Length: 239
Length: 243
Image (tube, rainbow over all chains, first blue to last red):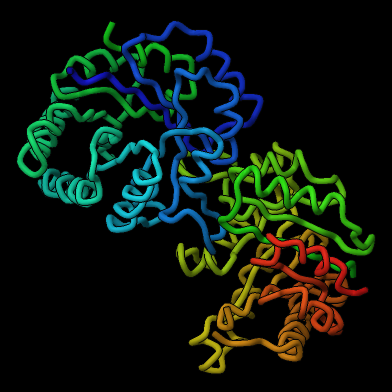
């Protein structure tokens, strides 16, 4: 009935077989809370390797995908390929995709619909840039990105929303509370009550506990710390 | 100049189907005078190098321009070497025109891949509107310049010409030879006599088992980058185009 706590780790463009095998060994052997759903996001070239080595209780996610099952798109991968090597999640609309590589709201929305129809779970990312926060348009910007995702979700049971400020715990709580209120008016009261909303700003072993105690924060998407031993402490943030 | 044939699988395959393709290639009679390379999706690169005969090379279909960092969704040359592949394809028409990759970015990628010890298949080519305006030469010389400014040792580079414009139109073998001959004249003078004589220039338009023998007889065509036919059994015939 209550929302289950969710922690993803985004490795970004880091690692080789030796270093990543060492990271996986540590997670497999650690004591992880039974009440946390854990997911690891690997570089595409190491996704098969990661699924082979990680304990089955831990999920594996691609860091990006395209919007059809096959075709003339040199350099891309599809949801069919991701299922084929046994991973169940994909991260979509990450700030680095939007702002370094120029991916639009429309494209991201199409990726979301296809991934879900193909039987993947989706971690959908939204967030405002520095110039946007300074202009006072935080809410308008994130509502806009959220609507472009929701118009492409027929069933919310396998969707998790991730808020990243691209640039305190009380400021995070304020944005999470308003996002849930959006789900209530524009979708339904039931969808608002059951959907996980995780925080994707800077998360470390030092700040994870206070963030996790906020009423509308359901977990994290972790960056640089997902490559270190302190990732274990972040998974156990509520204990 | 040793004959060179690459096969670009693009976004196609799963473990079953690509496994079958590799088995066919391992068991075929392939000319000893052809250098062969297979370009796999990133998610299957390690798999492909494990399964393919060591005489056949493996290429990534794209990479980025530093060894590590905050670039969600990307891979580096260090990662490609780590799983045992020796090549990368850079500046493919689909990267340029569907995903918007600039000449400046492609040039930075070429310099990094070569410094890190990979070979590079560098792609150039004009669009249909450019062909109609009569500016084919101007476009490919501009693209080739942005590559050459970033190359020190040409023994590790192969240049691929793609007529994007034709791929509902057709490109003839004489038309391919005319472009290849001009590209070599560019190299003679902007680099050296020795580099023009020794660098392979391969054709990346539509290659099938039916047209490969006439294309391979041209004086300045050194081989191919194959698309859809790299996924079929006739890829073997293309490797053997000079017999």
